[PDB]
Length: 106
Ligand SMILES: *[C@@H]1CC(=O)N(C)C1=O
Ligand SMILES: [Cu+2]
Image (tube, rainbow, N blue to C red):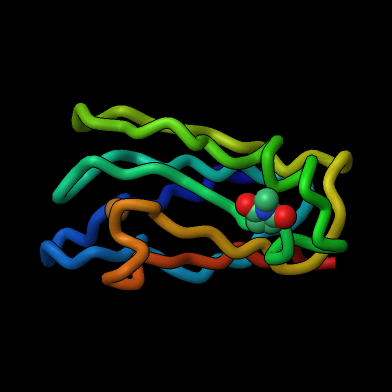
């Protein structure tokens, strides 16, 4: 049971999440922190999550924009969640390919 931290906007000043791709075990915590070049948000698409479950995507996505620095959003992948690859993106910076992927390992 750990806690992974992802910065919304690279310290370099690029429009990415870092680390972009992550690998976690069930029970772990993911914490996005507002870093460089806000505003950001976190969206999963209908058919990017395991099973393409719309309700799932909408349960995880923080559709609301975050503006102040240090502002954070947390998801804990308890046993409740299925395994596979969850793919997410910042909506304002979709064009610039601000994209990340979390894989749930076994
Ligand atoms: C993406 C998946 C879907 O069916 N809708 C309505 C989306 O926004
Ligand atoms: Cu962004």
